[PDB]
Image: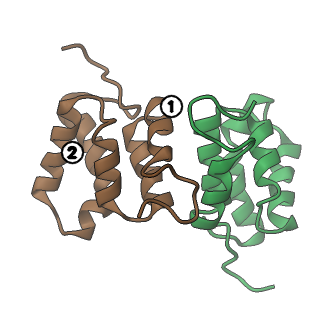
Chain colours: A brown, B green
Amino acid sequence: RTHGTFPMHQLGNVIKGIVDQEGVATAYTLGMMLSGQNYQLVSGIIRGYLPGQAVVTALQQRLDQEIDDQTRAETFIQHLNAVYEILGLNARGQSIRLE
Amino acid sequence: RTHGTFPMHQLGNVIKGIVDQEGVATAYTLGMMLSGQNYQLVSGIIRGYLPGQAVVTALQQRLDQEIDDQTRAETFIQHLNAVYEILGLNARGQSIRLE
């Protein structure tokens, strides 16, 4: 299951378009509102579109902490922004610092 | 012009899917981030997907006040939420009151 109302791809149309335009956390967010609270889908989709291994690591780190099963989702993007805090990304999934 | 990065319809795929799922102001918002700050496009697209004539009226009302040309866009969804304040809608483009 990927979509019912929003004309998503076979997985996450919203996600790609947004990762480039607004960044992963928005692509993530919109994947959440459009596809539903299907954390599995968004995390699977954006994980490949995540800035680098660090952003997914940080996000996974948040998931490792796992507040709950659904609460992962509830705070999934909050955790992605937390990611931005961890590694130094901005809202656009871009790095504001140089490594 | 409707889209370049995000696989939008011939006008606003994001917009329909979202109006049902998250509401016009989000559909509006996402149309703004994905399609660009093309207020013309989002206003034209969502106008048909706006809850009722009242929500579009209120939004148009905001546009009537027009802070600037681009600033309409800048605050377009803020104005849509303002719409929600005008007529009694919630964030989902739904009416929280009965007429």
Q: Let me know if marks 2 and 1 both belong to one chain.
A: yes
Q: Please, is residue A10 above or below residue A49 in the view?
A: below
Q: Is residue A20 visible?
A: yes
Q: Which amino acid does label 1 sit on?
A: Gln
| Mark 1, residue position | A21
Q: Which amino acid does label 2 sit on?
A: Leu
Callout 2: SS: helix
Residue at (50%, 36%) from the top-left corner?
Answer: A17
Say the numbered circle drawn on residue A41: none
Q: Position of residue B6 (x, y in %)?
A: 57, 37
Q: Is residue A33 left or right of residue A74?
A: right
| Mark 2, residue position | A59
Callout 1: SS: helix
Whole-Å distance between the Cαs marked 2 and 1?
A: 20 Å
The subunit letter for the residue under badge 1 reads A
Front-most of A37 and B4?
A: B4
Q: Number of callouts in the render?
A: 2
Q: In this view, does B63 lie to the left or right of B80?
A: right
Q: Is residue A78 visible?
A: no
Q: Is the Cβ of the residue at disc 2 closer than 8 Å to that at disc 1? A: no
Q: In this view, does A72 lie to the left or right of B66?
A: left
Front-most of A60 and B9?
A: B9
Mark 2 Cα shell of 10 Å, populated few (<14), some (14-19), many (≥20): many
Residue at (21%, 69%) from the top-left corner?
Answer: A69
**Quadrant of res A51:** top left
The subunit letter for the residue under badge 2 reads A
Residue at (75%, 86%) from the top-left corner?
Answer: B98
Front-most of B84 and B92?
A: B92
Mark 1 Cα shell of 10 Å, populated few (<14), some (14-19), many (≥20): some
